[PDB]
Amino acid sequence: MKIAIINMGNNVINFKTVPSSETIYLFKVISEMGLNVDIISLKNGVYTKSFDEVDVNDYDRLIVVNSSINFFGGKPNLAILSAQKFMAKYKSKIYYLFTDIRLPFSQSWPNVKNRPWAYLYTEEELLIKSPIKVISQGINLDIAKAAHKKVDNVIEFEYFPIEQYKIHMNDFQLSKPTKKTLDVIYGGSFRSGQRESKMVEFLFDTGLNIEFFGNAREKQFKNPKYPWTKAPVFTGKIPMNMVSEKNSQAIAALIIGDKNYNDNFITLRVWETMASDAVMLIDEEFDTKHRIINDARFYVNNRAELIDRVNELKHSDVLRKEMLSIQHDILNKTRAKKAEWQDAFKKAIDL
Ligand SMILES: O=c1ccn([C@@H]2O[C@H](COP(=O)(O)OP(=O)(O)O)[C@@H](O)[C@H]2O)c(=O)[nH]1
Image 1 (cartoon, helix red, strand yellow):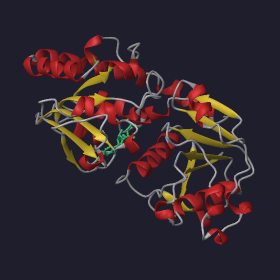
Image 2 (cartoon, helix red, strand yellow; image 1 turned 90 degrees about the vertical axis):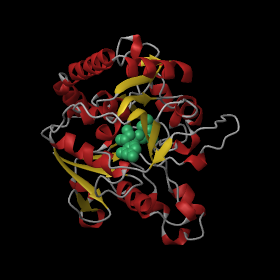
Image 3 (cartoon, rainbow, N blue to C red; image 1 turned 135 degrees about the horizontal axis):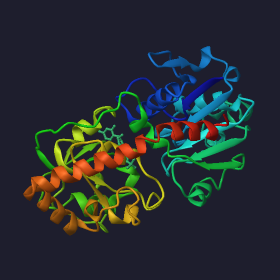
Image 4 (cartoon, rainbow, N blue to C red; image 1 turned 120 degrees about the vertical axis):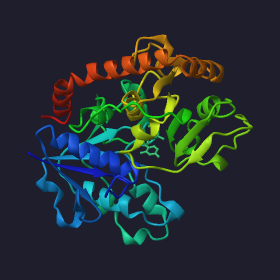
């Protein structure tokens, strides 16, 4: 049982970028599942085998991590064309991992077909005809299914909490009590504007000491419908394997989702915060049924409620330690089901 795993639009090498870290993380959790896995990427590396040194049909399973089909500057994107050429030539079913609601499986030939350098490829070489199995990180397959309106070869949809890989990795540990230097923290990118209201709502004009580390830049927050005067401190991106440690320098850390993730997806970020020394403060809208933790102190409705909750946390160390303790405990109850998650994942990839 040889499994192949690939990022459909991103080069994989180390943990300096999120799309490469997510792929490497997955390869690990699968390998620790007792499975035999190889990551296939642009060039050979510490975790990767090169696409043109491997014949995709040697694997009994091709798992593909989501990606856009965006050709920056309109110019060829080797990550995309190499991966699609790779997938197009596999004869069996493809397990597409849907971790981001913004990256449905999509066919590149349509794009390419119309670019000026089209002649450099052929339909035969890039059109994926194999049947696809979408594995949804979100519990709502109508949102998953809706997202893949335009693609026809996608005959199967299944739910699987893919992002729990982080809490299931064998090297996992909860963050230790760290010296506080921030009130509230949040890491990520701008999401192409997909979450501007929530980010401004909760991180701008709060009066608190807040940082937003990631690929998000202040200049991107320019939508008139969502005005602000005081933006948080935007630092740069840090490796995916440092996140909890970063998160841990803040009293609290923020959970906000895209409108479609609400009561739908549980995101990687949720575990990254729950395993950290920063108290988890979730937007009430993101999980209205409090499935993440059943205590209303972990949920906030607006900027004002968030500011109030941090004030209480800054005031009562007892309440702060108590809540981290609760979230840490609650995190482990899920980790206690590591086996059932391994089994479910296997079943999901037809094993
Ligand atoms: O400097 C940073 C900021 C974010 N992340 C990763 O990016 C993820 C969040 O990605 P996104 O902005 O798409 O947010 P989401 O939609 O997942 O909440 C986090 O969970 C981290 O794993 C990271 O590795 N380094």
